[PDB]
Length: 401
Ligand code: NA
Image (tube, helix red, strand yellow):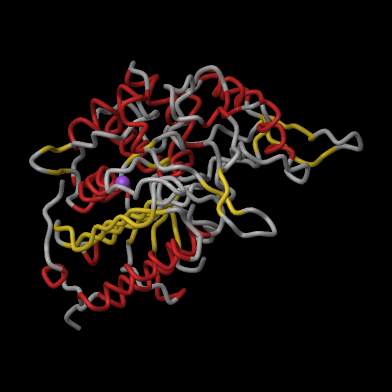
């Protein structure tokens, strides 16, 4: 459900694009993934859309409408939700987060540890700003790591921040737990977008899943995008795999039932809870290339999209993951400020992210194109495929000088 085209209509070599098909098929043959789905589009037309391998090992083939846990790739969708409330005048980037979340008046920061292993806690210099929350520079800790080296992360893990009974609970816990750092000091991947999801609930007066269905998924035609997979769509859900240590062979992932996508979550996570299809995500990506509109439906003003896809980071900062030199960070996505500085082939201003289950995307406004990759494989395989898909896509692209 985007117009199909020949590769040459998007400016691609058919022969060199086939090297991307071959590479995906090699990853299935060598048992690195069960299967996956890829969409490449330029000038609003699909140039390549391909399903590979199987939905489940020794099972049916991967359908193109397969449903995937996008994890941290949910993040930029929450960012679009926040920017809709921005256009309605409900929050400003210079606003203290404490105006929206009053309990954040009680924030404390972890300084050192004392002799008894407990963090030394100090009232925060000031409330983090909304721009810091949108850019992972607000000083919040991470929620999936038992790191004795990072006391703030260990406390979040121990308090079970990400498995709270509600977003109200999650945000009350964060208010009482130690921050990793004072706001504005460094970029560090955090629970910031899960806190953003609470602000959507509080400002919209609707639950996060309802607001996103009404303002994003319904208007853009994203039919299978949600915080769970209803019983009828379960047969299209791709299975999640990990590598057996010492065999390097595909094994069902064991991750705990809090992440289960069979039921509506109690605390829907704006940083990691969405499931989607390559086609639904392709529609979202085309809406960003079109600066806020798809098929006559406008969800954001063009200036608002332009503001999201710029680097909002101070001069100095280091984006340390994409799920490097010349990398910055906009509103809930990475921004390639100067890709040449790392010999990256994407155009300057390219936005991207990826999830822990292996999913990745990039949108390149300078080259009017996007790539959506969907697998369900934990570990380093996803990030390797991202880098290799970027190399093979730009080697197939033929531009004027
Ligand atoms: Na799909």
